[PDB]
Image 1 (cartoon, rainbow, N blue to C red):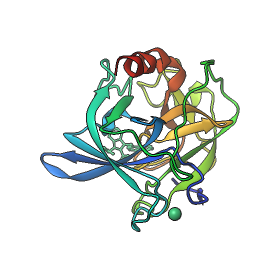
Image 2 (image 1 turned 180 degrees about the horizontal axis):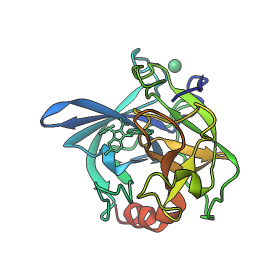
Image 3 (image 1 turned 180 degrees about the vertical axis):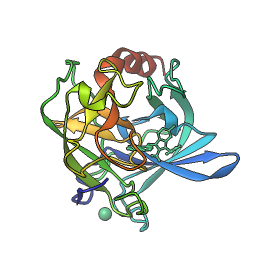
Image 4 (image 1 turned 90 degrees about the vertical axis):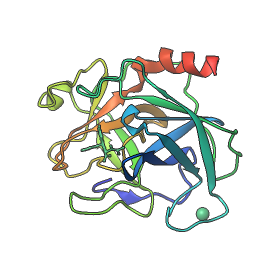
Length: 226
Ligand SMILES: CN(C)C(=O)Cc1c(C(=O)O)n(Cc2cccc3ccccc23)c2ccc(F)cc12
Ligand SMILES: [Zn+2]
């Protein structure tokens, strides 16, 4: 998160910290969010050979009683995810057991409504990602308020599509999701409407988020069958 604030500790109890293992490099990291006691939603580009989930964190360097370190038993990457275009950048993680409900750990289920969110409003995104181009990942959960932009603001991303994705962050400001924030939720009036997907290496906003409303049928299908 660039240009944001430290979150009040445990104030976003659905937030998930993901460690992603591959066979031929060290760990990579993403965010995510708990939508059922045994399901985390995140980005498809966060898939790996194996994933660990930590719920209940604020400072990810200091173990505390709120932590729940949970095993993932299966990854459900969107079947039409495209590594070239990055269309359909969405994935569900099924946890081996249901998480415990505590003050610091809780679900964020979707409301029944799945209305298309137009440009114009402010929304908030949280993550443990880098706080600038040359800066390491944050040890503490950070958050920032960002403007939903008209789709023409994201035209330079030649594979961006308005139907599939949100365009997030006023280009006149530095405020943005960035590397290490992948898979984290964008909340608009307390409702998850986006997932951090990608943007520019040089951090100039806007960035591209998966538009959750488009994927609600798929999410429902996976949850009901598993
Ligand atoms: C498992 N991970 C994490 C990786 O493989 C590295 C990775 C990241 C990242 O580091 O988070 N992001 C997000 C990202 C990248 C570049 C610039 C961005 C500017 C804004 C927002 C997000 C940005 C990816 C998007 C597509 C992809 F195929 C891979 C990645
Ligand atoms: Zn604590």
